[PDB]
Length: 50
Image 1 (cartoon, rainbow, N blue to C red):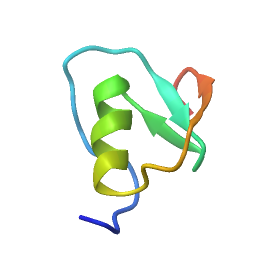
Image 2 (image 1 turned 60 degrees about the vertical axis):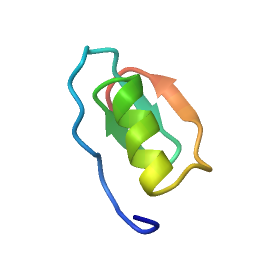
Image 3 (image 1 turned 30 degrees about the horizontal axis):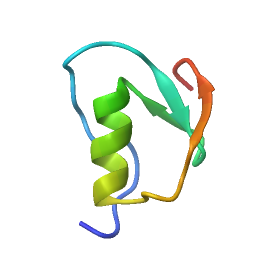
Image 4 (image 1 turned 30 degrees about the vertical axis):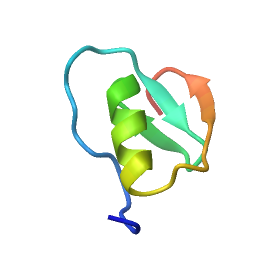
């Protein structure tokens, strides 16, 4: 994808985290999938939905 913004929806489970973009991830899969498509370079900012 290269350039995509927001969250990419995955729903295997709900462990919410926030990415360094300040973005709410529904679960690890959300963080992984969205970033592998968009921004692999951010880190988990904090545990819990943003």
